[PDB]
Length: 201
Length: 201
Image 1 (cartoon, rainbow over the protein chains, first blue to last red):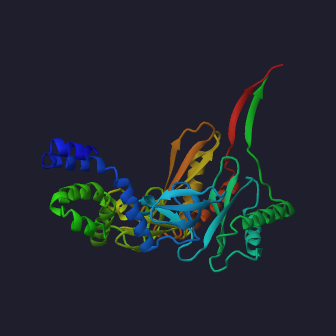
Image 2 (image 1 turned 60 degrees about the vertical axis):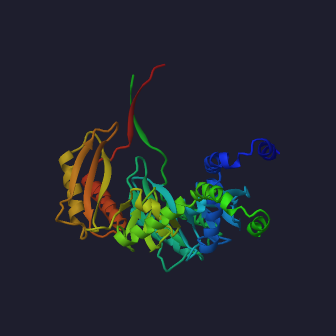
Image 3 (image 1 turned 180 degrees about the vertical axis):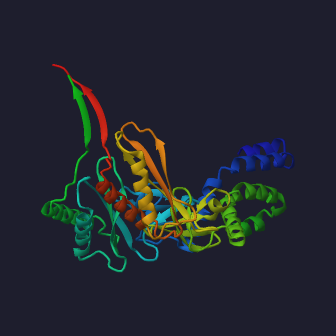
């Protein structure tokens, strides 16, 4: 209606078309964030860097991608808190996916040992607990590492492997239970924080 | 279809081509993030700043680069959490690579000693433990440094060298085990946190 009113009285389309074009660019630089999203979605769909069913972490948002679209991707979190992520972050921003070519993952079990202990006994107990599990992988050998002279307790890390991304927590539960039972049986001290006080009067 | 309908009724291509060009730039500034990625990938491929098989750290993401492409680079993390990084961060953003010209690295072993100890004895024990290893390099001499008058314990650092980037942790394990054994043998006190309390009533 405004265009018709202006044309029927002023008729200056050939006069304000340049202003229209300048305003058009100055105000259509608002669609960059949308067209980039669309192009990123198309690129993701064509290249297939992530597939449906794997675990993806981006921006401290780890979860299983459920549906992929041309505008936004839906990731079901571990609490079914559906996260909607623009595909521009999927294309032009770095991400992590845990199931790409080998669907295997290593996990660490950290513990502290008292200063007056037996490092060889602790290593044997940890290795036996890791090996006795009927699920941990054997081709990559699980190892125990002495990695830190802690302020109160020496730090020990057991880096061991799981080939299934689903049960990454039940294995940790069983391993920790077995480690605690073996430590209690073999009398390995897991000391608390320690300090020395000098007192007078 | 819309173009044909507009042309067959209005025929104003020569009238809205300027608006088309303005919108084209305003909405094709959405491909900057993609073309920069492509050009960065091409530049990385030509210049070869990083090769396949070395260890690269960028944005707190350290791992071994597996495949390099024109759009995104794949880095297998230490947990096989495949990180997909746009090559724009590889070209226009700083990074670190541990295997460029000499594939060697120095590592530090930190420990604390009690105030009432023998600094010369501690230095001798640390140097003997560092030297007795059959892997640490000898051309750069390993040294022990007294670097901090700590609040509770004096801080000692052993900076020693490894020429292989693969076994950077097993050497640390063996060195720490040997250091602990030698300290226990020679009676060197690794004190905990200490404080003094004044009490009354």
